[PDB]
Image (cartoon, rainbow, N blue to C red):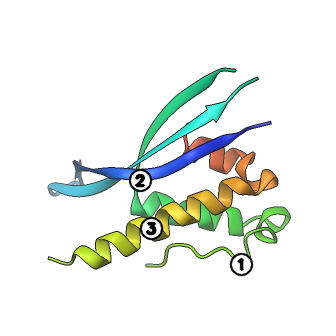
Amino acid sequence: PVVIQNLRITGTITAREHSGTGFHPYTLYTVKYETVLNQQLAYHTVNRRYREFLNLQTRLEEKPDLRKFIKNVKGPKKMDSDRVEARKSLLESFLKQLCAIPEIGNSEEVQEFLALN
């Protein structure tokens, strides 16, 4: 079914959320990727915070029929150019690896995260 290609993080967006007592900036990672139809091609963009990457992993791990596929996938855990790069690469790598596994890539959890469905 879903053919995802060329996933990568191209940058960030800094947004503000309100906590009740005040407004807080936070960082969204801009993920871009393509889906192939058969010779159509769709361009997709989605912005997700670090916390949403974490939740995605947790939601997958919460499911036995899925947790089993990603046991060996290295994912997120709780100036400095090298940290930023390491984290970006880690987050991309995580997403590429999830999407190469058919049972995972086609899961509603990933579809929703990438805003495909």
The residue lying at 25 percent from left, 57 percent from top is 26
| Residue 16 disc label | none
CA gap, disc 1 to disc 2? 22 Å
Image spot of residue 20 (x, y percent): 22, 54
Dot 2 falls on a residue whose secondary structure is: strand
How many other residues sit within 10 Å of disc 1, few (<14), some (14-19) or many (≥20)?
few
Q: Earlier in the sequence, mark 1 or mark 3?
A: 1
Near-viewer residue (63 or 66): 66
Q: Quadrant of residue 94?
A: bottom right
Dot 1 falls on a residue whose secondary structure is: loop
Image spot of residue 70 (x, y percent): 73, 70
> Disc 3 marks which amino acid?
Ser
Q: Which residue is mark 3?
A: 89
Horizontal side of 50 relative to 62 (left or right) equals: left
Q: Earlier in the sequence, mark 1 or mark 2?
A: 2
The residue lying at 80 percent from left, 36 percent from top is 1
The residue lying at 66 percent from left, 59 percent from top is 98
Horizontal side of 30 relative to 2 (left or right) equals: left
Q: Work out which quarter of the rendered image holds the C terminus and state it.
A: top right
* Relative height, residue 20 to residue 116 (above, below): below
Q: Which residue is mark 2?
A: 9
Which residue is outermost to the front? Answer: 39
Q: Nearer the viewer, mark 1 or mark 3?
A: 3
Q: Which residue is mark 1?
A: 72
